[PDB]
Image: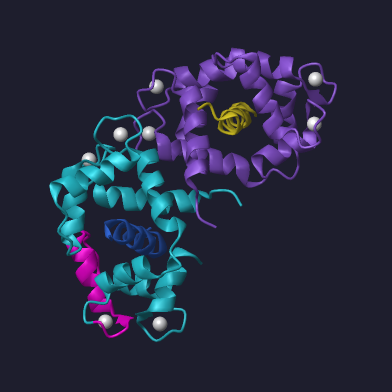
Chain colours: A yellow, B blue, C purple, D cyan
Amino acid sequence: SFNARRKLKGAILTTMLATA
Amino acid sequence: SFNARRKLKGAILTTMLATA
Amino acid sequence: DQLTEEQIAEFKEAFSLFDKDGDGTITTKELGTVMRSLGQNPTEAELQDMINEVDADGNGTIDFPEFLTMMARKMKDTDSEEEIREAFRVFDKDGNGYISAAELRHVMTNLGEKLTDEEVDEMIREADIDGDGQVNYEEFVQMMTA
Amino acid sequence: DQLTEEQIAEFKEAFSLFDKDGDGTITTKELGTVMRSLGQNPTEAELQDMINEVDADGNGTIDFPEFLTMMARKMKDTDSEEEIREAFRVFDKDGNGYISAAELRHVMTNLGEKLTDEEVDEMIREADIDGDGQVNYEEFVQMMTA
Ligand SMILES: [Ca+2]
Ligand SMILES: [Ca+2]
Ligand SMILES: [Ca+2]
Ligand SMILES: [Ca+2]
Ligand SMILES: [Ca+2]
Ligand SMILES: [Ca+2]
Ligand SMILES: [Ca+2]
Ligand SMILES: [Ca+2]
């Protein structure tokens, strides 16, 4: 089943890498 | 340069996986 | 204490947002795609620089370990709050201090993720320590730490 | 606290001892090879079972994230000491309670690693908290923890 915690953490980590 | 700590840790971790 | 199975899955999810073709490697084209989706405008030479910093095997693309290394360097020393605040602003587009459900849906849509209203609400719930239905800065920070 | 760059390198080193052809995937043949080198005798069905427990993408081989997941499960709950003691015994071949330089060289040779006397001495030094020139059980444990 969709794991919202994993989904949000993955998106946050991606956004951190995508930062200067 | 050869990193003995990494080498020994890698070998220990491998041996743990290779255990029952 | 030990890297956990769930931590690994979180990293794998992040890797998959870049590796959209699921071939197991992140190219400069894929890096660029994600960054522009998040409102950034890296140059080609800047994308090359990012890959070269971690391209241990010199093959010009990023594999899983190299991606983890990129992450580990990023997450190392964040006390200035400069980087975290930059990431929060990506989500808090109106600058009001709270990531709304609508704002989270904007970012997930930009990242190429199809999600229902219920899924995105569950994401908010995960971060929403104080129960107000929105994610503040401290809640965002805690999602990385926690 | 955060997965570190050095932790990643340690895991990558372990992955490379299995992935001897450096193609980025561990096959059942490679798993078997390492295990037999370490005095084990897994059956084919047992090797398949190991891969199936973590083969998220169903491709019949182990990639980096799947390898990390295998490790994370192994390292999870080791308080019985059964597993750690089994791994220590691989190195402490004469059962005397201490991993000697010669014993470490035996295992590294079995794993296919070419090392000098100086390199292996440096490995002992890394684990040898009490300075006696050999690695005891508690020192071995601390190498995984530490
Ligand atoms: Ca790709
Ligand atoms: Ca590479
Ligand atoms: Ca807002
Ligand atoms: Ca809140
Ligand atoms: Ca291989
Ligand atoms: Ca697989
Ligand atoms: Ca011994
Ligand atoms: Ca000692």
Nearest to the observer: residue C140 or residue C126: C126
Q: Residue A9, image x and y in percent?
A: 60, 33
Q: Residue C44, image x and y in percent?
A: 51, 18
Q: Name the quadrant of the C terminus of chain C.
A: top right
Q: Residue D18, image x and y in percent?
A: 25, 49
Q: Residue at x 61, y 42 (%)?
A: C75
Tell me the quarter of the picture where residue D95 sits: bottom left
Q: Residue at x 42, y 69 (%)?
A: D80
Check residue D40 for magenta coloring.
no
Nearest to the observer: residue D132 or residue D79: D79
Answer above or below: position of D74 versus C30: below
Q: Residue D39, image x and y in percent?
A: 17, 64
Q: Residue furthest right?
A: C96
Number of marks present in the image shown: 0
Check residue D97 for magenta coloring.
yes
**C29 left or right of C100?**
left
In this picture, which residue range is highlighted in magenta? Answer: D95-117
Which quadrant of the frame does ligand 2 lie within? top left
Answer above or below: position of C106 versus C52: above
Nearest to the observer: residue C18 or residue D48: D48
Q: Residue at x 39, y 86 (%)?
A: D132
Tell me the quarter of the picture where residue C111 sits: top right
**C101 left or right of D21?**
right
Asked whether the viewer can see residue B7, the reply is: yes
Q: Residue at x 31, y 67 (%)?
A: D87
Nearest to the observer: residue D21 or residue D53: D53
Answer above or below: position of C25 versus D44: above
Q: Name the quadrant of the N terminus of chain C.
A: bottom right
Asked whether the viewer can see residue D126, the reply is: no
Tell me the quarter of the picture where residue D135 sits: bottom left
